[PDB]
Amino acid sequence: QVQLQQSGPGLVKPSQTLSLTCNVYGVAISNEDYYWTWIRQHPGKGLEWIGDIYYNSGTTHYNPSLKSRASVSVDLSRNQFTLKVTSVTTADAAVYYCAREASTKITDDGGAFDFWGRGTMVTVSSASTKGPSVFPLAPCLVKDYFPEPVTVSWNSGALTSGVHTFPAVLQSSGLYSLSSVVTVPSSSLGTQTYICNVNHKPSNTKVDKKV
Amino acid sequence: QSALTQPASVSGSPGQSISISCTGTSSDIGGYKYVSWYQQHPGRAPKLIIYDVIKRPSGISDRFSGSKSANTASLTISGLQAGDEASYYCSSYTTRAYVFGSGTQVTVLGNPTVTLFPPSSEELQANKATLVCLISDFYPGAVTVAWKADSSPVKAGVETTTPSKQSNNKYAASSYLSLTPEQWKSHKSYSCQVTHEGSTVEKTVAPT
View 1: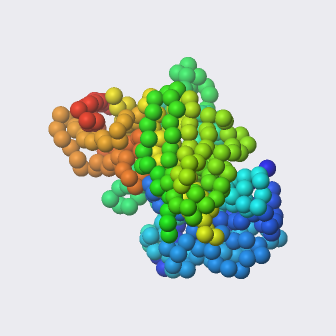
View 2 (view 1 turned 90 degrees about the vertical axis):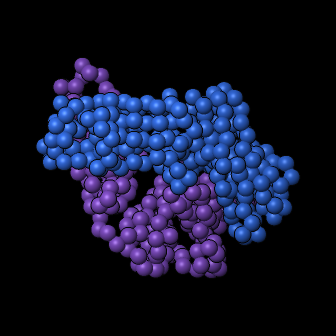
View 3 (view 1 turned 90 degrees about the horizontal axis):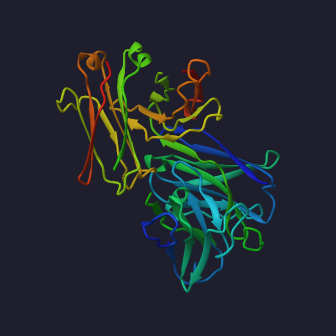
C-alpha cells in the first residue's frame, strides 16, 4: 500500500554535502500518524537511527553522534523528503535507508518502521566514478568499476537460477570487480539468448551484454 | 545513549526453534510496549517482522513470534529454514528517540563449496586474464584462500575478500588472480586452495 523510492548520488567528495531523496507513495508526508526517518548502516555494522521529521515539529530529533550535521527538507507537492549531511567525512560512508515510522498513537504497525526504502550506498572519496567493463563468461564478472555497488540480473529478471552474487574484490588501483554465478540447460544455449544486465547506479551506467 | 543488547550470533538446525534476546532498560523495552523486530538479508533493506512486542504485520508468517519479560524482548523463529539465515535487529521507542539493537546473525546449519572459473575468450581478447575463485556455504566464517600456479605459490595479482565483522555476507568469500595475458596459456595454471579449520579444499582448474 506504501512504497518509498530513494535517489541521490552514490559518491560524495570529502567535505561536500550528501543529499538523499525519498519519494513517498501511498501516504502524505503531512499525515500526522507518521514520522519520516533516516537510518544508516556502516559496512558490516548495525542499524543506526539518524533522526526523523514530523510535519508539525520544528525540533531537531537527531542521533547526537551525528553532531548536528544532518538536516531535512520536504517538498510537499512532490511528497518527498531529503536528508542533507554537510561537510562529509569518510565516516559518513554507509548505506542510508529512508523509512516510515508509525506513531505510537495508532494501532496498525504502531511504533514501528513499517516501510523502508531500498537503501542508497554512499562512498566518500575523491576518486572519480568509473563505469564497469562486463565480461561474458562463455559458453558473469564485472570488472574495474568505482564506487560500489553493482547489481546484476539476467534477461531482465526473467532468469533466476541459482543464484548467488559473490562479494566484490578491491584492486590496488582502487577499482572493484565481482561476479555472479548461474547455470542453465546445456541444450538451450546456442538458440536462446542470454543477456546480463549490469546496473552501476553510481556512474548511472547500465550495460546489457549478450552472452 | 542507552542501547539495546543482542547476542552477536545464534545458530540452529532446520526445523528447530530458536530465540533471540534484546535487553534494554526500564526506559525502553520495559517502559513501553512499542518493541519491534526487523529481518535483514545481506545487501537488502530491513523488513518489519514484529511490532508492539507480539504482533505480526501483513505478509509475515506465523513462524515468527515476539514476547517480552521484564526488560528483555525475545524473537522466536519456529521451524527454522535456510531462508531464515539473516541478521535480526530489535528496536524500541525511548525518551522521544528510537534505538536499534546491536543485531544478531542467525545461522541455519544446512566442506567448503569451491567454484573455479578460468579466464574466458572475451577477457583475454581484452588484454586481461582473471582467475575466478568463488567459495560459499562454510561455517564457521574463518577461511584462508591461498593460490598456486605451476604447483608454485603465486601471489602477483591475488585479491581476496573473506567474511569479517565489517562485511555484509558472512557466509561467502571471493578471490581473483588478475594478470597479464599468456600466463594462463604459459602452463596449465592453476589451483585455488581454501583452508577451513582442517578442511583443505584445493581445487585445481586449468584452462588451455
